[PDB]
Amino acid sequence: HMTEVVRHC
Amino acid sequence: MIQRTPKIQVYSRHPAENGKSNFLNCYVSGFHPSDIEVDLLKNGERIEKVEHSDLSFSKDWSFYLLYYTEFTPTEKDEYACRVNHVTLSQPKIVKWDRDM
Amino acid sequence: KEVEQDPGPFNVPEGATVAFNCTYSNSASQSFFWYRQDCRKEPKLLMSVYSSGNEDGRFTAQLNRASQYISLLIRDSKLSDSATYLCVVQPGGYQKVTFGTGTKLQVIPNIQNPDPAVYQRDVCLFTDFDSQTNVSQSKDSDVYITDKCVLDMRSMDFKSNSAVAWSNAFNNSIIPEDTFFPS
Amino acid sequence: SHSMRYFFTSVSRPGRGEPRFIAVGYVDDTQFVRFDSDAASQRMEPRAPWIEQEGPEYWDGETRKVKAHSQTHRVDLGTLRGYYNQSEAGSHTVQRMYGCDVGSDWRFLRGYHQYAYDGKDYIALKEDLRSWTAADMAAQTTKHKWEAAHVAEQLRAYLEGTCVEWLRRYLENGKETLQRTDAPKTHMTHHAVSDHEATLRCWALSFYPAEITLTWQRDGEDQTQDTELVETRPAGDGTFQKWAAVVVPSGQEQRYTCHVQHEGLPKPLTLRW
Amino acid sequence: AGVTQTPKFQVLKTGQSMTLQCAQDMNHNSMYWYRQDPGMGLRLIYYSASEGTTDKGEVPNGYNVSRLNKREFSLRLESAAPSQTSVYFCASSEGLWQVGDEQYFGPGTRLTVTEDLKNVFPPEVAVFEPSEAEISHTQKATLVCLATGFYPDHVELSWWVNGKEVHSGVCTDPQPLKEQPALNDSRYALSSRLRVSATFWQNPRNHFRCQVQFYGLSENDEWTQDRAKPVTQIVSAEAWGRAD
């Protein structure tokens, strides 16, 4: 189960 | 950017026994970046039904794959693994030894 | 709607704390915001809202995933805080954002020295009343009255409420008993 | 005793379309899922039988999330180029690895989220799951943005919660094959190198997990002084293989002992020619 | 800078067609078009997650969009209906795929569609001088201004004191009011108020202007009836310090 927490570096 | 040469290993899945169906592996690891050519050779001709693992990488960030295909050895048929990568001036051919 | 909030409006005295709340249906919802929108203007981000209550100055926002609400607290509220506050959710990546219908906040000054009055050039101007006074509309279709409006004279540090009428006009509005009616 | 990892790789290929994106998901040393931007479905595909049992809602969201990872990676390539004043023409790589470990007790130990650019460390979440090691000065600009938007908090949540919850679900659902330990099928080979020197290859075959140590000893003294040691390689079987070789003066084979220690062996093993 | 959106106001005859523009220089991937109506919130019309693609939102019926490029995003009204009167907002974000994706909104576009362009009128604008009683009782004087008769409710009232625009001392109604609360296409009223010193009013040198910006018909809108052309104009009313 993958996170939803990805944020433009 | 860093550049890192692949480490090739050729080996069967199961101990080399003539006229029995095994799989012939070629594993490349420790390279970067990820663009790589890998052909398996029967007597020096590319095989055609060669699958590969999905691209992954290890702690140091460097990449690894497994190419492989069903086959039967015959002590007669010589097998190898040809590899090109940016780091390499010429392709590398490493033979398949049943002992090492 | 994926989010609900109470429309109000909520009248808070200038200086008092106000608390707002929004509830949401979908427990999976990952990201939350409060937005602020002035009358006839565009929504603008106030702040994002995380489980670790972020106190930023006068503002504090809280998310409670367990109970599925988010809150906004404003300390030392200012006249300039009067607006509609919107709760906003982004469920997660690549999902549509929903905008709440919004809670209106009105910040109400204390009039230190009421002086309720109705003047009349070329309109009657009901002025100088305390903040508990409310102006209602006229029973007469050809009578026009606008709602209480608050002016600040920044220099004299003085505030007043005004309501304009046009065509003795406020006989449908409960106005104070001591209202000046010169003539 | 257990972990879940996701590895992501993103390769700008300027002039040849959108970047290449490969995503793979592991429980321990077993791959269960994949995504390849260059394959045909454009969906998260199963890669182990025990995951095929998951419902459409699962496959939907996994697909949604990975697409969301690609886009993030796709923008990241842009900004990182910008940050380093590099050119539109060169191909660069971005890598992301993240996961959670658990003990034999299946509770949380440790979460991690690491981010590389062109194969160097670029940003990592600390082990306190609250701050970031920013390697370069450009990574510093990344870190400010990630602070301003509370990425660490949000990750700590996912890492200590849903991550481990699902890893457990996975371990439960894949018992027949994820709970296994397979001890090595060790043997020994002898090759005449010189007129006066042999090799001793000590073979460990078809074991799981991957983690293994092969050492050599000359009369009990831990002999690295002539030790060749290849990388743990996969068999395809879903097993692993490894060896280790020492050159010895012909006639003194019998003073050398291989020492194999795997999770799957009660006590360390010892072979001698 | 940020998100720009043009035009700010607009009138349209039922059946007429028209396109709103929006651009952003924040290098954002995702852009959106929303409309606003009392009672419900913002309703997403269409959106454009990225330079390539677009997609319908919650209420696309009547509208289309073109993601002209990474920068601009336009929303077309094919044939304006009376139900399309509303406030439209463009907005943009780095990318809807990321967590915490703040949206940045444009200033909005207020849009009225009317049964006929003969309904559009400018404001009559009166100033009214402070009461003799007021200055007597308070030692302070308030001029009220009254912009009346206009349609559509598209106006910007400001007070001008010796040709500087004043913010202190003033209260304009938060929004205009429907003179005729019954009739569909009713004309609107707005009041404001300005308060000063009794001394500052009395001074005869001092210059007071209630200026209201109307938004009406364009240089291209076709006016054929006798009264003056309800174009985008300023109507002002003025007054000087008395003593009486």
Image (tube, rainbow, N blue to C red):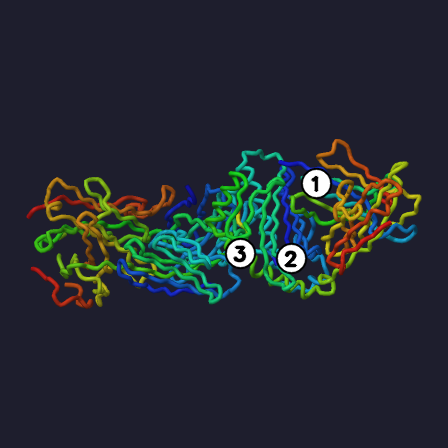
2 vs 1, front mark = 2
Mark 1, Cα crowd under 10 Å, few <14 / some 14-19 / many 20+, is many
Whole-angstrom CA distance, mark 2 to mark 1, is 25 Å
Marks 2 & 1 on one chain: no
Query: For this view, does C107 lie left or right of residue D193?
Result: left
Seen in the picture, residue E160 relative to C95 is either above or below; the reply is: above
Whole-angstrom CA distance, mark 3 to mark 2, is 16 Å
The answer for which chain carries disc 3 is D
Q: Quadrant of residue E114?
A: bottom left
Seen in the picture, residue C50 relative to B82 is either above or below; the reply is: below
As drawn, the residue found furthest toward the top would be B89
Secondary structure found at label 1? strand
Q: Identify which residue is drawn at 92% across, 51% down.
A: B19
Amino acid at pointer 1: Phe
* Residue carrying label 1: B31
Amino acid at pointer 3: Arg
Q: Quadrant of residue C132?
A: bottom left
* Residue carrying label 2: D3
Amino acid at pointer 2: Ser
- Image coords of residue E168 (percent x, y): 22, 48
